[PDB]
Amino acid sequence: PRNISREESLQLEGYKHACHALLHAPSQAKLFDRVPIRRVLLMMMRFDGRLGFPGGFVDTRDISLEEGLKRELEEELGPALATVEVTEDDYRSSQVREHPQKCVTHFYIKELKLEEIERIEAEAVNAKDHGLEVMGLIRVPLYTLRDRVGGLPAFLCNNFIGNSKSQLLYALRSLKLLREDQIQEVLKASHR
Amino acid sequence: DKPRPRNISREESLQLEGYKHACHALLHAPSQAKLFDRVPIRRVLLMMMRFDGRLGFPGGFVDTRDISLEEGLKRELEEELGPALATVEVTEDDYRSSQVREHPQKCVTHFYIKELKLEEIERIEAEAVNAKDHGLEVMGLIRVPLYTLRDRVGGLPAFLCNNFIGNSKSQLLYALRSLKLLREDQIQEVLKASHR
Image (tube, rainbow over all chains, first blue to last red):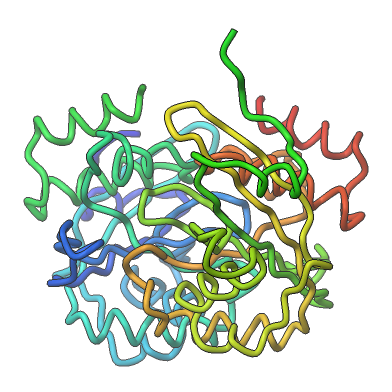
């Protein structure tokens, strides 16, 4: 809901912290041999029937934000994440809420090689949380099809948890995948 | 005066021209797993995220001339889910219903339901990542949450607020009924909670 610096949010007291990450990789694949995938962005279907980024609650008095994220990624995505290090340099932004509960959400973005993403998908089915906390991994379509709705716009009509949709839109800008006008167009198209 | 999406008999749907045919399936298996050690999964129902950003059931377009509806389905399932599907039966006994539509398409959709063993579902999930359609027509497999969480929205009702292709949402509701997972009044409740 509201922006806040990492350092600032880390000085707070009585707040619940959560760390989530977008793992992505460039791709040369083309849907139907014509529509470039451009980049693979991973999200998941949660136990609560909503889409979200992998990650979760982190007790900052016990462990760092990066340590907590790491532990949650392994449980959710599998041991493939043991070879993947999401660090402080991968940290992007934090948002804060007071109502309904005092919550800080930290968003990380980490680029990987396509083969690493593919290996993560392969081993996610053997993750501890597969079929429970995590109901499956999905890739985010970045393109808009000819009917001007299929793909990204339609995708944004799904049910996202918390500020995950805002985080995705943020990543689309920061990774320079879509310009501000293109984002507005995809948002408009999803609105009708 | 225009027609709308409506139920149609298999025989009738096959006895006409100008309409495209599609076949999709719900593959499912009983499970003893429990979420948070207390919420029974009860059953694993496979759906997927499509290339078009919508949720749907695996399957696709089928040529009524070439092979049977059963045959066309099994072929499409193999491209979407991987080679494990080649060994999967799928007969007329797995056929369930058909819907005809004209609205900006003119299409007939056939829905199938087939029970498999849990390990068979698990195998398909593992092999789906190496299927021809992975990362293309198929953006990932998902399991349908059947339970409703304590806040009375999380789980199936929130799941039902996602973006579903065509009549896949009706097909899912049909399945929850025919498999005796939920009564009609329970189905009406999840819809009500999802619309809230």
